[PDB]
Length: 251
Ligand SMILES: CC(=O)[C@H]1CC[C@H]2[C@@H]3CCC4=CC(=O)CC[C@]4(C)[C@H]3CC[C@]12C
Image 1 (cartoon, rainbow, N blue to C red):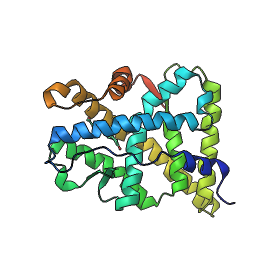
Image 2: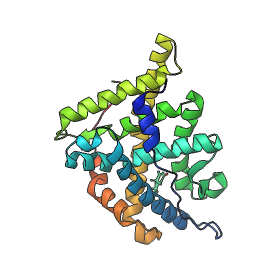
Image 3: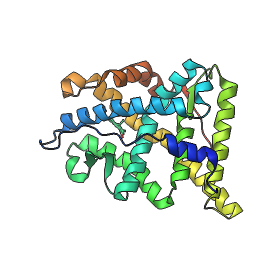
C-alpha cells in the first residue's frame, strides 16, 4: 500500500540471520575471536553474493563489474549490517556480530581490536541518533554496494549510473514514508547521504586492520577462510593505496 514495491522486494531478499558457529563454552582469546569473526565473514560473504543475484538491476551489469563491486564493498556492507543488528537487537550498546557472537566491552581485551570496535560502534550510534528506519537502511545498503568504482570506471557504466540513480530515488521514497516536511525530508536526505560518505574513512581503518592481520595471520594464529582470503588478496592493497574512485554525495 504505502511501502514502495522495490523496498518490499529488498525486505524480502534480505538474508536470514547468519550464525558464526562460535564456541562460547571456551574462554575467547584474541586470536580465537578474530578467527571466529573471519568464519562469520566467510558465511556473510556467501550471503552477500546470493543477495546480489536477487538485487534488482545488479545481475544486468557486466559480470566483471558485479564481481568488482562485491570485492570493493564487502567490508562496508558487513560493518553496515553489523551496525543495523546492533541497533535493532541491543539498542546499539553491544556489537551484535551474530546471535552466537555478541561483543561487549568486557570481551574486547585487545587494545588494538577494542579501538577498531569503537570505530565500528560509530555506525549503530548514528543509527540510534538518527532513528534510521528499516526502509531507509535497505536502500542505503544498496547504495553502499554501488559506492566505489574503478579509476577507469565500469564496463557497464551507463547501466551502473541508472541503477545508482534508481536506488537514490528509492531512498528518497523511504525517507518520505516518515519525513513529511519538504525541508525536513531534504535535511534527512542530507544526513543519510552524509553518513554514507563518512563510511569511506571508517571502512579504510577496517581495511587496514584486516590486511595487516591477514599478512600476520600465521604469527597471530588467525585463520582466514578461502573466499575471504581471495577478496582480500584481489583488491585490498589496491583499495588501500587509493587506486579506486570512491563516490561521494557531498563535495
Ligand atoms: C580479522 C580481522 O582483521 C577483522 C578486522 C575487521 C573485521 C570485520 C569487521 C566487520 C564484520 C562484520 C560482520 O558482521 C562479519 C565479520 C566482519 C566482516 C569482520 C571480520 C573480521 C575482521 C576482518
